[PDB]
Length: 225
Ligand SMILES: [Mg+2]
Image (tube, rainbow, N blue to C red; front, side, top):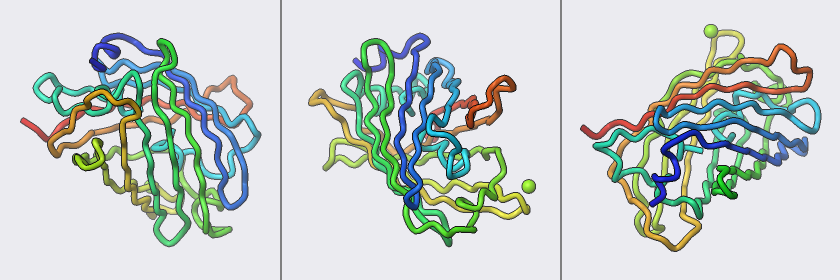
């Protein structure tokens, strides 16, 4: 059972290749997760140079298997149940009045390391919109991820709205539609409706000259008593 793999600290690797309006870039992340406390600490680096989109727009793309599921909800934790073989996460992120990202990620163990391999494609971004114009503040509001089972696909879907803060006090909405499907043939947990409550703190490494993002995230399952 998948959850047995998460009782202690697990190293995480994230590798993203992206193309947004033809701007190609890559991000490499390292860090660790402790699902006991729903805690992620990660540092992401753009290995191709300057990130052509704001870091906060990549937070959701850049391992919900590290959510803390309260014991009374453990039968609803799809993500860990899919491990170690993993799951494929597909998202469409629709930025209101602007372009969209489509992402595909394979999340699985490689040895004792949890790896998230991602391809991101962004299209129809406006040149001086909030994304390609870099008008988003370097922060991240707390939000819920709402999960529902997709039993015909042996997986789950999530929907949620991210509100990115624009530097002028306004909000850039990013609608997220997500589907997750197991990679392996083992049984997985198909949950009741519930949500993940998440909080993310973005920061910088003061010794780091590369374009990068330090992230501290807490994710807790809720919505079932
Ligand atoms: Mg403000």
